[PDB]
Amino acid sequence: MTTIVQPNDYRDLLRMFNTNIQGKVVLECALVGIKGIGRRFANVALKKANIDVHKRAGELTAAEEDALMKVLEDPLSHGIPAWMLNRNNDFESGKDMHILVNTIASTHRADLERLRKTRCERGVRHHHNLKVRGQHTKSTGRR
Amino acid sequence: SVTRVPADVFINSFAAHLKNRGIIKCPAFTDYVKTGVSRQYAPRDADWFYIKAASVIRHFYISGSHSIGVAGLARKYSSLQKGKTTPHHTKRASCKVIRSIVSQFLGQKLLIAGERGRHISPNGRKMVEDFAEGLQK
Amino acid sequence: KVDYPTLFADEAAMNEALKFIKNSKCITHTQICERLRVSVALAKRVMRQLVKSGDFAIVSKSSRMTIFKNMTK
Amino acid sequence: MHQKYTIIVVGKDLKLVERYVKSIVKEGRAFGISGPCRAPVRRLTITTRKSPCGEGTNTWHRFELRMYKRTFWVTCGGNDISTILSKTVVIPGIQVTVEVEEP
Amino acid sequence: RNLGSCGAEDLDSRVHPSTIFWPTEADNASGVPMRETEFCTHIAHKRECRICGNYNSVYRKYGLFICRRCFKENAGKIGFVKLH
Amino acid sequence: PNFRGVEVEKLATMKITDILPKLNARCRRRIGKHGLSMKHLRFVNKLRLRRAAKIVRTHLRDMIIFPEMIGMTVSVYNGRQFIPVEIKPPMVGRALREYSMSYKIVSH
Amino acid sequence: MAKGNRRDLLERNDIEVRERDKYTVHTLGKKKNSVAVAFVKAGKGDILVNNVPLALVRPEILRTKVSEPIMILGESLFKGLDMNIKVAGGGHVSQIYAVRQAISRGVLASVKDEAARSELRAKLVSYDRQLVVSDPRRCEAKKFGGRGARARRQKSYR
RNA sequence: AGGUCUGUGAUGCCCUCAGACGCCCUGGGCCGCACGCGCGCUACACUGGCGGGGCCAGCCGGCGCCCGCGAGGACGCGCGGAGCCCCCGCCGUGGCCGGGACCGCGGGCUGGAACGCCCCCGCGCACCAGGAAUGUCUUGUAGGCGCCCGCCCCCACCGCG
Ligand SMILES: [Zn+2]
């Protein structure tokens, strides 16, 4: 903020995690385009990383950029609460981590594969294209 | 006294003074809180704790010998929960921050303990009125 | 359909943006937004700078809207 | 002797419940029995469909039953248990006008 | 079967003897402990109109426990009056 | 694979209490606080007897799984007949309701 | 929270007794579920509301409405009177209107002369008559046929 | 020949009455879904969304301390009320910070038993004001905003107020 003329380093189009962020929107909300990153996990992440959260995305710099990258892969090693992670627990690791765009596809997919082999009820309704939670389908959401 | 000056100026000025004098000291959990289930996002300003504390102390001064519980203050910060394809329903704020604030105030003898809850100690009344007259001009 | 920069690259922020209004008497953030062909927050900040300069003054400030006047003309 | 006794009158009908107090205060003419506090009316309410089978335009009965009550705690220990019985006998016998005495 | 049981390690999982929280409503039957073993072992409230043995559409307000349909017939005597 | 990082080969003969603090709310509640009930314990004891020494049919449809029951053969009721089911490691910490269909899929 | 008809509010027992007596005149004003009580004593001149200066009452935009009984007349008589208003009821606007009504009625009484009182009555009532006489209309009930006082649930003839 | 024999120790005549349509116990179902529509709820944004703060109702009404982000939890006693709205800032016409359906880990409550209900992180569907047709309404009224009771182990987009 307190900026009228653009930075000499103004990066007009940012890129991260295979996703591109335009450098004219406020910083906290622009980062939301990343899948797995919302608002709550945004304003918290930057602040631990010593970053102004009301400055345009185009104004940050590498040193700030990389610093944010680090907290974003090993967050629990930075104080963030364990009840805040998107994956509050994992089936095989047994720990608590935060997953991102690159590996968020294999989080509902491989989950489904587990459902199939076990022949659970929840998996079947996922195959015939039906509701999973207790939901009335007699007249709801007709296709 | 306070009652002849609007809350807008008094709260902010007392907050600045309360930060300068080091009366209250924001704890660590002020980093990642939303202040009430009713809300959705987090406070934007960087010193909401001290504003909250000053509003609370003013509330206690206005209540005189009456006593206010920690929850009683939480119903005065309630909001409306939206985004649920159903009629909006009211909800209460958070009580932990309020509890920490009253503890910090009581540790400074500005807040006496009563039979239920607490009320403004005489020196607390003195201080509140003193800042009120100081800023009245 | 329409894209507006959120900050002048350079020059624009004084050659004209601080001058187009100078040849005006009344104005508002939206009036300039439609006039200058840029976003609103830029108009807000620029008007702050101008009032600090002292040329532009206020007549009816409010959260929703703040009309200005070119006192120095 | 002295007991800080209490008098409570509970009933539904405004007519008797108001006439009975007049007799009570007559009887307490000299024992100092004074004005009674008249509590807010406890208007009990119930609603019900008029149709046992739920046919036709949906209509609703609205019955309510009020519970007037008055209190003559004035006596307190001003009177003795000897004539507290006397307090309870010279009074008229109304079929339904429940009353109870506590200290 | 009075001289048998399970493993001790399993006994730790016995339900807390703390009395069950699902009682039976009694408007005013002494609480006392072959077919007797399970005549009505299942425990559940059986609130019903104290006039007609019907468990459907009973008001519990003010401790009435009267069927809505059977309410109209006796309301006049019970005291409720239809005004306003 | 594993189970919250716990091994499988040792999962045999491995105490249910130890694993209990590694499961979700429902298990840590029912098994711990509220406790279990007689019929279920009799069921488990019967299964132990068989494994020590035919498929155990049962009406129990809320009998949270134990870890030592890996590899067992148990049938279950669906309101009309009896279904077979076999327990696999990743299936541990769950009920038997999910593995017995009461309705049937719809087709045209 | 307060009903408005509580014995405490009507008698203003909140004030300490030694200061209760000094107030002579008593006045009343209301609009809809709102009751405003005013006590007057002659003095240097000042007003209060729920323990607040008259100026800093927060509809903000309605300050002139709460002060109309004053600027309508001259401040000559308002100079010699001091008020301690206490209001309680439903809605900000209702409280405002009740307060101005109470102010008007209270100032009218303290004149102590009937002819000048009638003259002030004529002056004030010429402007908004609902500055002295109260407003009667009040909220009505709702019937089971619809979901409002007069509106009815939509009907499908087919 | 409108509805009610499925409200009743209100009832005529029929059917059932020791492999029971009697009463009871364990499970399942009444919620199942290519589709048609009836009463409603949420929205399609700047007369707005988010954050901080100030503040007033009535049918009526229960509170303190301590843990926990929150929902909730252990103790101890009799004590007590809101949304709209107003003020200061951010957003700036972009299906975007409008919208919150759907879905994945997790933490709790009721209950003998979750398929029931809450809170947290994450994903972010249609929707750009709706054709032929059609409904309701004259003062504290329409409309907008919220708050209690009913059935209720848990739950209100419903109904009475
Ligand atoms: Zn009945």
Image (tube, rainbow, N blue to C red):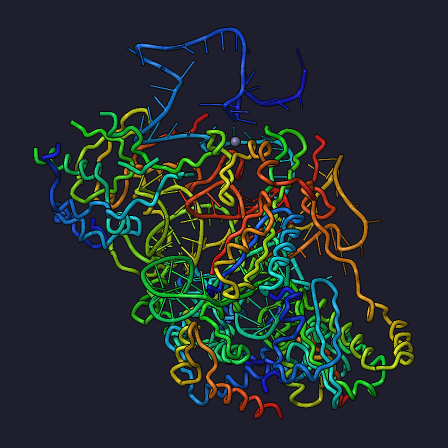
How far from the left and from the top, in percent, is residue D13? 64, 46
Residue drawn 32% across the image and 71% down it = A79
- For the residue pair B3 and A44, the one nearer the viewer reads as B3
> How far from the left and from the top, in percent, is residue A28?
48, 69
Residue B117 location in percent, x, y?
43, 73
Q: Foreground: A137 or C67?
A: A137
Relative depth, front residue between C59 and A51: C59
Residue G129 lies in what quarter of the image? bottom right
Residue E49 visible to an observer of this rendering: yes
Left or right: A22 in relation to G140: left
Q: Is residue A100 left or right of residue G29?
A: left
As drawn, G39 above or below E67 = below
Reply above or below: F90 against F82.
Answer: below
Comparing D60 with B48, the one in front is D60
* Residue B92 placement, left or right of A81: right
Single out the residue that lies furthest toward the left.
F53
Q: Which residue shows up at 58% across the image and 44% down it?
A: D96
Is residue F77 positioned above or below D15 on the image?
A: above
The residue at 67%/45% (across/down) is: G147
Task: State the count of labels.
Answer: 0
Look at the image and tell me in which quarter the N terminus of chain B lies: bottom right
Residue B81 appears in the rendering? no
Q: Is residue F20 left or right of residue H155?
A: left
Q: Quarter-wise, where is residue F91 in the image?
A: top left
Figure quadrant of the C terminus of chain B: bottom right
Q: Name the spot of residue B3 as percent of width and height, x first.
A: 61, 83
